[PDB]
Length: 37
Image (cartoon, rainbow, N blue to C red; front, side):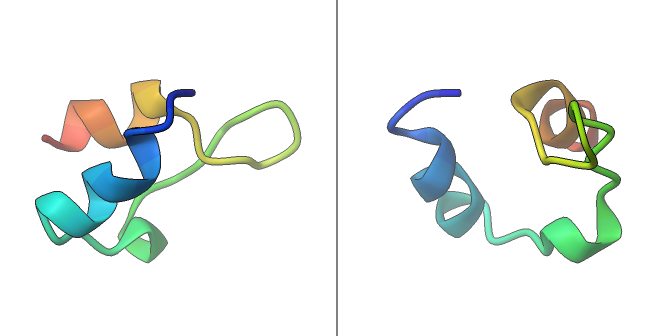
């Protein structure tokens, strides 16, 4: 992740609730929201 990942959701205004975080344990990574962008 990066220090800009947090502001990345507040920049494009997107609900992570609609995105699936298949991270290592059900976490939200960047390869998940990106596909949505």
